Image (tube, rainbow, N blue to C red; front, top):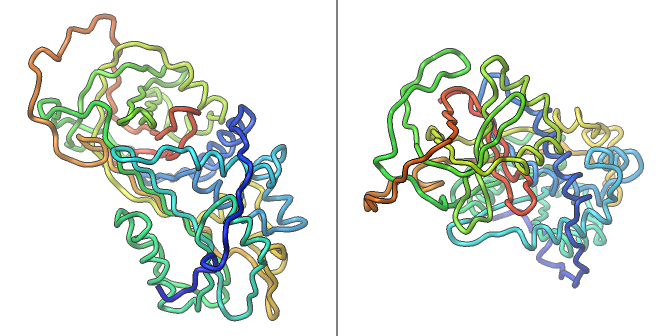
Length: 387
C-alpha cells in the first residue's frame, strides 16, 4: 500500500447483537431485487452482489445528512433506520458462513482524497463497531489506482485483481465493492456427467459448450418459469437457476420480480427429482452503480452541489460527493463447484432410477442466484445471455 488506512487508529467497542427477523429479511430482499432489475444488462452477462451493495450504502448512510440521508434511507427502505440497519447488518455478517469448501468474500471500502479532508471520528467509530471495513485517505494519483487494485487482489485472494483504470481530478470519494466466492458443490459432478451440447444465446447463435448433468431435489415452478436449487458444501449456500418460459424474455421476466416473489419462489420449490442440465460458465462483471442507485432514489449523493456528507467529515475548498460506486463480482460454475476437475472414482450403483421426475435444461438464457440458505437472500444475482 501507499494510501493510509484510517481505521488503524480506531478500536472497536463491544456492540449489542440484533436478531435477524422477518422485517430485515423482507427489506433486504426488496432492496436486492429492486437493485437487480434497475441494473439488468441488455447485451451481456451480468452479475451483482446486492448484499455487498447494501452494506456499502448502509455504512455510508451514517455519514449523510438532511436530504442525502433521507434519499439513502428511502433507497434502503424507510421503515428500518440506519441505526437499526447497522445493528442488523453487524449480526448478519457476523454469522454469515465462511469456511473451507464454502468461502465467501465481501470486500467493501471507502477511499477519500487526501488534499482538503478531515474525517469524522464518530463516523469511523461506527465503521469499527458495526462494519469492520477499510477506510482510506489517499493522494488519488496513479499510485492510488494501483493501491485500490492491489487491495481487491489482496482481499479476494487473487480472484479479482483490477477494478479501476483511472481517477479523474475532481473525484473525492469512492465506494469500492469486490465480491468473490470459493466453494464446492455438496454433490460434485462426475466426469461421466459432462457433455457437449448447444446453448442457444440471446443473439440466436448456437454455441457448443459443456453441460453438467445431475439429478437435483428442488424444483422451482412458477406461472412464467421453472428451475432448480443446488446446494454447495456444508449446505450454507445454494445455486438457484431460474429458466423463464420460451415465450418470455429474460428482461421481461426480471421486471416481474419482487423481493417477496423471489423469497417465495424459493420457499415454495417442491421437493421432487429434477434432471438438471447446467452449462459451465465463468465471468466477472464490473458496474459503476451511480446510475442504478440514482434510479432508486439516491440522487443528491452523487452531485457536487447538493451532496451532504457532513456527518462523515468536512472539506474546505469543495464539498463531499460520491464520484463512483465501483462494484465488481466474479463467479465460476464448474464441475467441483467453483473450480474445475471432475471426479473419476465412482460407485457404480449410485445411479438410481427416477420416476415422476422433472427436467430443467439450461438450454437458452436464464437467471441465477447464490442464496444464503437460512434466509433465501441473494448474495449474488446474475444472468446468462451468451457463452
